[PDB]
Amino acid sequence: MILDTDYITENGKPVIRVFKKENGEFKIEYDRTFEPYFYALLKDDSAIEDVKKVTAKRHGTVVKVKRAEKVQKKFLGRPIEVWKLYFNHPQDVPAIRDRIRAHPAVVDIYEYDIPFAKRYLIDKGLIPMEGDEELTMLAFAIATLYHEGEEFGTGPILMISYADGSEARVITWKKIDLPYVDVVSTEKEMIKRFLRVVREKDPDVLITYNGDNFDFAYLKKRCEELGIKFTLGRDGSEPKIQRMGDRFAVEVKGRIHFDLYPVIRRTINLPTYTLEAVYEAVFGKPKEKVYAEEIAQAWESGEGLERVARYSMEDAKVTYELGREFFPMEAQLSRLIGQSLWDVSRSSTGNLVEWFLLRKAYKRNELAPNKPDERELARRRGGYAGGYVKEPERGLWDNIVYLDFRSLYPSIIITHNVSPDTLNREGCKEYDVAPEVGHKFCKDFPGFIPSLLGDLLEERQKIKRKMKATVDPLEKKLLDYRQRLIKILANSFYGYYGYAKARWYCKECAESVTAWGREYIEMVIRELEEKFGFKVLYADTDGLHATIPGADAETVKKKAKEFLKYINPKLPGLLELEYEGFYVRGFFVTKKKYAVIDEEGKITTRGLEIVRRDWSEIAKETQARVLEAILKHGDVEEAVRIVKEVTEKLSKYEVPPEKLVIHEQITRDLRDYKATGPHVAVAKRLAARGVKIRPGTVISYIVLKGSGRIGDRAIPADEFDPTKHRYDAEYYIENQVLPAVERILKAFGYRKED
DNA sequence: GCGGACTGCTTACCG
DNA sequence: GACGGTAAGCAGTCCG
Ligand SMILES: [Ca+2]
Ligand SMILES: [Ca+2]
Ligand SMILES: [Ca+2]
Ligand SMILES: [Ca+2]
Ligand SMILES: [Ca+2]
């Protein structure tokens, strides 16, 4: 299985490296054959040799075009003949391009911004992580003596924990007398040992939880300060800390550095992303957190380093268990997209789509359109109409049937051949015209994107069939990950059209998708209301809730099933409506906010404060208990009482602190903010202490007693101590518990609760 | 003047 | 880190 690709420079010539593992042995295949290239559309082929003599200096010396060949290749379907300009070293590409482009003979420079290592994987048609081979993995974690506002790295590492299938152990230089602790003599000697342990085990994968930003960077700062050759690589390389986007990312050449944080963040939706939370979330089993204040006084005292140790050991043990559960699906991802597990792990669905197209485009002889310049993105800053959301018939309704379209936007993208290479073509035999946008899509050639979208959905059914046949539970799991991933990639294509920084951007494509969406949703609703006697209670894009007021639950079911038989033949192409659920009773509050309870008794909650992370857990609990009473039981008085007891408990100061924590994410650099919410006021005072309040950072806080602006009275949950502080018993009753509860119980017009 | 009515910023959800 | 549509709360500024 091809792990990843890289290139070194042997005697001033770029030699490619394909890191593979064949028959339970890591092998490195070199390739000097592959020469870099980039395309160029000259105004007149006559000016080939004239424009071929452009140059500019690199670090070593001057760079000039090695050779050039005029090539025929399709662009948005339309045939085009352009010059591909070969260069000796890939780092000559970024030097020559700007000047070669400015040349008043060439029209534009194309396909110049693809890395060579990634170019090789595409052009050769080599698929990463293909074939059956069990890869050895080692999870590791570090514990540091980082002070309050201490310059990053000055604090020394106290312990290094590593864990795999066999064992979990701690290496440290203070004396923790336990069977899983290895006492070294100095910090230097423990790092020396850790590096040796990694060398001895020689694992294919190194698992971390946010190792990209903290763990690896910190080990470097120390290895510099102490003077240790930080060689974790298989080729004897020190780990490469690249500045990928807002954050950084770290590559251990020869191994897979699998940072769980970015993957877990993308996958799971949690209030906070502590390794304690991620564990308790995924596995359900709890994990205690030995703090920095504790880890410090432990080291300073010597008393009770056994807890500080157990923590470090459990951190690695958990990291391993999380890694072994997440890695497999992130591997099948690598296969589907066709780039390394490393990239696919740290990539947006936005870029995963573009990588998947760049690959298919090469195979189709399609020249890839360039990413937009700064002036272009400004021109793509024009929004478009979304989908229909019906203003809901409010109240408690009985016997609701949920109907929705199966893969709506994809069905449209396929059916109407929606693609930039088909948008308003010249003299096609057949066209499909968008309802209100008016955009006409050529229906002669199967479009680039639709063609691929078909194959994906076409393969997903092949995989779901092979799953039925699969006897091995492991393969049936790995097969489910593939089929599942295909779907999520298939539903990303509408979004990619609207995404400005996308190569294959198309505003009129995205506009037309939503438009057809609006028409078909509205047309279904109209029929179910007219032809059949249903009353559409609420509807969002692609889905609706309805019932037959006064009819029995059985009748609602039968009649809804009868409607699907009627409507589907009337609908065109792949546009098909499906019966998705029936619910005993349901409650619609506002647009995007409602709840329903199924026949078995499982309540389903959408949009209400219960699900939101930026509400006090007392408000989210108090609501869920009121909502349970109204739906599950039916005791409206019980809800009235549930509010009052909870309300009195807070005013008596008997409400636990833990339940009062409010979580609000920091969107941008705190300076850029135009108006200060509490979370901003919390973030700005925390940053004044030299803390790292950066984009992605979730701010926890509690409202302290008093009056005025809520933001000037917010002490972080960690910072908060009971003392004589207490809490703003008013706020949590006035602004949190009551408003949220009121939303549900307002249907029966309740005024005030004690 | 004062304080109730408006309005823009920001967050997190829904599909 | 895709998309647009939506409900809110909090902290400012009108204007009768
Ligand atoms: Ca020009
Ligand atoms: Ca539903
Ligand atoms: Ca099904
Ligand atoms: Ca019941
Ligand atoms: Ca948006």
Image: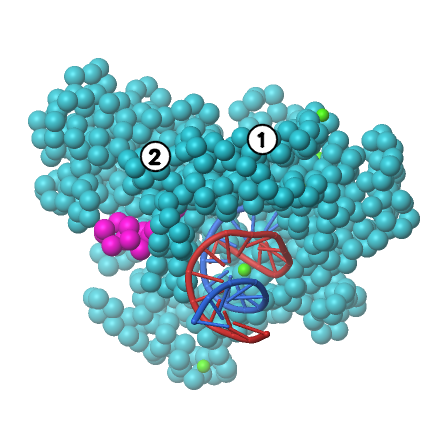
Chain colours: A cyan, B blue, C red
Residue A131 seen? no
Relative depth, front residue between A180 and A98: A180
Q: Which region shows up in magenta? A: A682-699
Write the residue at 20% across / 16% down. A178
Residue type beneath disc 2: Ile
Residue A604 percent location from the top left of the image: 64, 35
Is A32 drawn above or below residue A563 in the view shown? below
Is A478 drawn above or below residue A531 in the view shown? above
Report which quarter residue A297 is drawn in: top left
Write the residue at 48% across / 79% down. A107
Q: How many marks?
A: 2
Q: Is residue A685 magenta?
A: yes
Disc 2 under 8 Å from ligand 5? The reply is: no
Tell me the residue that label 2 is attached to: A207
Write the residue at 18% across / 42% down. A147
Relative depth, front residue between A100 and A164: A164
